[PDB]
Image (spheres, coloured by chain):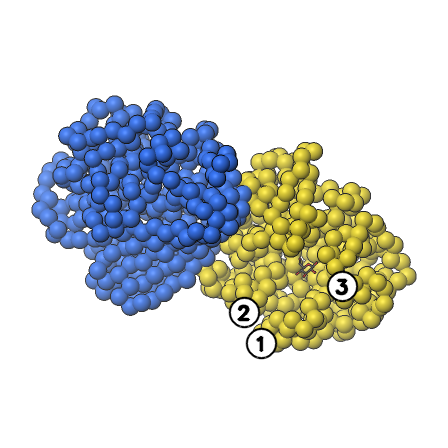
Chain colours: A blue, B yellow
Amino acid sequence: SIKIRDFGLGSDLISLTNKAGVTISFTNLGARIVDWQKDGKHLILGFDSAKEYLEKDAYPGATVGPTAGRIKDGLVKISGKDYILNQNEGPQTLNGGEESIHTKLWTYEVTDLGAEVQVKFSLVSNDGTNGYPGKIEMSVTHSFDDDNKWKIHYEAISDKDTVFNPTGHVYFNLNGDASESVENHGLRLAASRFVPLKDQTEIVRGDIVDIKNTDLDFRQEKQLSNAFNSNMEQVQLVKGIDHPFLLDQLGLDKEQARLTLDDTSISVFTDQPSIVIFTANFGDLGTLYHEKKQVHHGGITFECQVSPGSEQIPELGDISLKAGEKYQATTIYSLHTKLEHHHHHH
Amino acid sequence: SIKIRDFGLGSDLISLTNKAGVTISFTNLGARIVDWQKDGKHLILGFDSAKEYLEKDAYPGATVGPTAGRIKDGLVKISGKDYILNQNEGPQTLNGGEESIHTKLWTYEVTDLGAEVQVKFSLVSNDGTNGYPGKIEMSVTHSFDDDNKWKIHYEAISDKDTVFNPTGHVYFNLNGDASESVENHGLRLAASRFVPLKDQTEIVRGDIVDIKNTDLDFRQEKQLSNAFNSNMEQVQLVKGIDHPFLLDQLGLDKEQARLTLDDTSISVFTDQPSIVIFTANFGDLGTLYHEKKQVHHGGITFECQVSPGSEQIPELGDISLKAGEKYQATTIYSLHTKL
Ligand SMILES: OC[C@H]1O[C@@H](O)[C@H](O)[C@@H](O)[C@@H]1O
Ligand SMILES: OC[C@H]1O[C@@H](O)[C@H](O)[C@@H](O)[C@@H]1O
Ligand code: NA
């Protein structure tokens, strides 16, 4: 079933319930996921109104772009030309600059296919917005089906050669309480290499490093605490994880990642080449989620996209988008029960 | 009473009914007025859903900006520097460029003061948006009161020196039907001068012309048919009226214009120096409003703002907005019924 109501400030909340009784909800404020519950338990982090997002933290569950991550000194080269984008994190352009797409009300239309329901959100980034050539007509379709798959499909077309590499900023927390660290979750990730950050400014270092057999190796499932407890320079630098992981095998067909807690798992599929993982390394900030003070490590993202730093490490890919060419990306989060045996204690 | 409902595409329709039973409704799509009615009759033009505005005509009742009107060659000088804005009508930048603020979903908050209810719409125009320096934080507050006063108050702040001169694009039609020309309405307007257009491109001609004692003198109430049947080359040029009129006496207290049809009249007040009047000179277009095919002259606007063309005729004013300065503007449309 589909339900809709005002969510505040003019945004709406679209709630869907599939045949298995699983519920998922979105808001057109930032074409974002607000909640996902199973048997009354939240699987992700989210707020109860639109104003909370705007006042506490506007990234959670959002669609972010046009370019996800940091761009050193806001400088991109588009078709032989240098373009400087909005710099909102020091000289860096983080998640498309200030007051980006995640802060706007997108128009939307809902399509009921029965076993699947689609919520297609649209927005136009005008030419020159935040320094990006355009205009860019974008659309994010979020869908949920009877098989517990939440899918994100991105599409875009630009009038001019530009850059495009958006992502979904959901944070999971299988504990269903922000005040509980995810160190107790099991993580499996099909990636043998990662991208180190230069320093606290978080721009990329310049090299690609192999992590096999290190505390960042999750090819074979392990508790997140292993990473959190690590004293590897990169973990210390960021106080947890906040890096891109390069997938070893590409393709929407492979389970790239799996996050488990007891009897629940979330599997990650995508057609993108990397997964940027950030573990809510907020220290004692304690942002309130549903009246619970969030803890350091109280959440984890799986932002599938082309890795950040390709400006410096060409090997990571190319995010340019040619005028008239159609951008498309697909990411999927599927929910499962009793997929494996995960019985631990922390 | 206040009622909020879905207007389509995720937009909302906010309807306010005052003590007199008069209803006015707005939508966050473009911080715009959708309807205004009394005793079941519409006073203004509007559609029945969001999609209509997007498909038929996105301007009606909307907040247009950041600059209202046409800018020659899309060119403006900011701090002695030339900037080229988005060109969406030939080489001109019309009403802020393509996909401007009138096609965006603004956030809003309703504030009920009893005798008055206010609806504050907000939107951030990112720096660089359509060539404009920013970011510009804008807000448009539409309010309605028990005295039948509909008021528009604009406010903006920019991080960088930029340009700013928005307007409300409501079209009135006291006939309450688009298929009926407003030629029967009577218009009074406190302006002795106007700004002629160069030609069919509608850019300014370059001069300011005295209208005293011409078909365009409305200093004394007159029927619109008069202007409409005029042979003045300017009327003939656009097939009606599509020009900036310079107000004689500036200030919010003075009734600047008055539109009348029978016992129903609309008074316009503003703190702006000019009023741009366009008489829906669409010819055979036939856009449909409420299932009624619009006729040529089936509407009229009162766009209060600084006259377009100041890039060429500096006497007109100056639309710049320096970093950190707070822009404010107020326009009021007041409804009266003779007894
Ligand atoms: O919370 C916003 C951001 O926090 C930063 O510290 C992370 O590096 C970003 O990747 C994330 O988008
Ligand atoms: O910009 C709003 C209106 O302005 C007039 O100058 C034009 O002639 C109209 O076609 C247009 O819809
Ligand atoms: Na809505």
Mark 2 touching mark 3, by CB under 8 A? no
Residue at 61%, 60% in the rendered image: B59
x, y percent for residue A329? 34, 50
Q: Which mark is residue B238?
A: 3
x, y percent for residue B145? 62, 59
**Residue B152 visible to the viewer:** no
Q: Quadrant of residue B75?
A: top right
Q: Earlier in the sequence, mark 2 or mark 1?
A: 2
Asked whether the residues under marks 3 and 1 belong to the same chain, the reply is yes
x, y percent for residue A140? 39, 54
Name the amino acid, label 3: Val
Q: To which residue does mark 2 refer?
A: B48
Subunit ID for the residue under disc 1: B
Q: Is mark 3 within 8 Å of ligand 2?
A: yes
Q: Which mark is residue B291?
A: 1
Residue at 35%, 31% in the rendered image: A313
Q: Is residue A154 left or right of residue B17?
A: left
